[PDB]
Each structure stands twice: as structure tokens, then as C-alpha cells.
Image (cartoon, rainbow, N blue to C red; front, side):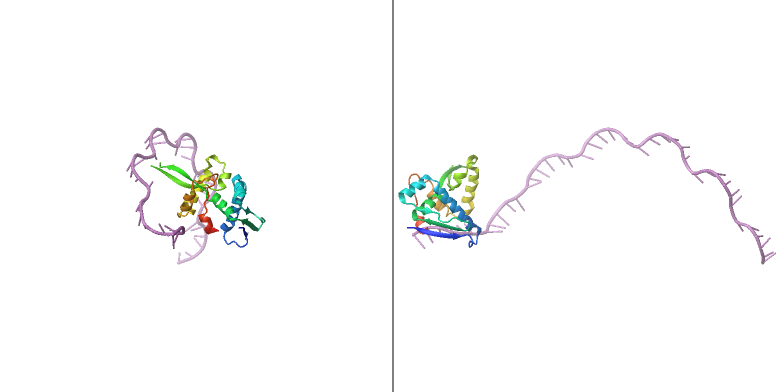
Length: 153
DNA sequence: ACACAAAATATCCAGATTGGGGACACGGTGATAAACATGGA
């Protein structure tokens, strides 16, 4: 189906509420700049359109497939191997649009952001339950997850 | 027992010299613990 949402910045009580709006706008724009997103739109009829973009208000329209694609991009994770200084691997999220803008030497700035994300915001195992299962998937292979999307939808 | 008078001018230091030589710490350590919050069937 089609689901439409509208939001205003004059009623949000927390700054993080306002920050999330810009974050999701950037995520949608990053989706709009990926060929595989257009391939998904052509095949599964993915709907994700920003209607109103002004100083105060915001509007969005999306379907189930668009939400699934957004979740796949945002919650993409991979596996990294670490050696003590007897081997151990650590699951690390991809980072979303951060990889698309980080051109620094070795993406060391990305490393700091990834460490904080797993370490504090995601200290609860909940990131790991969601993050580890998601990890290692291939977008080009059509891999997707929708068990959690149904509850959110 | 009466009265009168009770000091005046010159001068009050000159030279040479006021420290020198050596040294201003050595080692060992610079806290240790206990006091949780969210998920799926």
C-alpha cells in the first residue's frame, strides 16, 4: 500500500528528534543516489518520495518495500577480524551514508564513529541481535530481511 | 648683714685598601574494590 507521514519541527521537545529528521532525509537522499535502489524500484515497485521540503514542515510517502530498503541500508553490517596484542571476529555495522562521504586516510574517522556506536548506544545486546544477523548480507545478491519490518510497519 | 660684676676669637683630620679557591645529593615505590539494563514467546 501507500503510507503518508507529515512532521513539524515546532513540536519536537528534544533536539535528537530534530536531528533524526535530517538523518533520515540524508538516508533517503543516499538511497536516491544508488543504482541498486532504482533496480529495486523497477522490480519490486519501491515507493519512497519526499513531498514537502521547506523551512519548517516535512512530508514523506513510502511503501513496505521502501521501508525494507531503508532498513537494509541503515542496518547493514559486516564482520571484521581482530588479533589480540587465538583469533576473534567482531561484527561491525557498515555505517550507511558515512562510507559514501569518508575519503580520509584509512577512514580512521569512520573507525571512531563505529566504535562509539557499538560501545555505548548499542551496549545492550539488542544491537548485536539485530546487527549480527544482518551482517555479511549481499545487496547485489538480493538478500533482504523483513521479519522485523512487519512489526514496525 | 647692704651694692656692683659671672667671659671674649681662631680651629673640630688628611690616604691606601673591602677576599680569594672547591662543592650545592645519592635510590625505591607513586592505589585496590563493591554498588546491570534490555529483549521475545
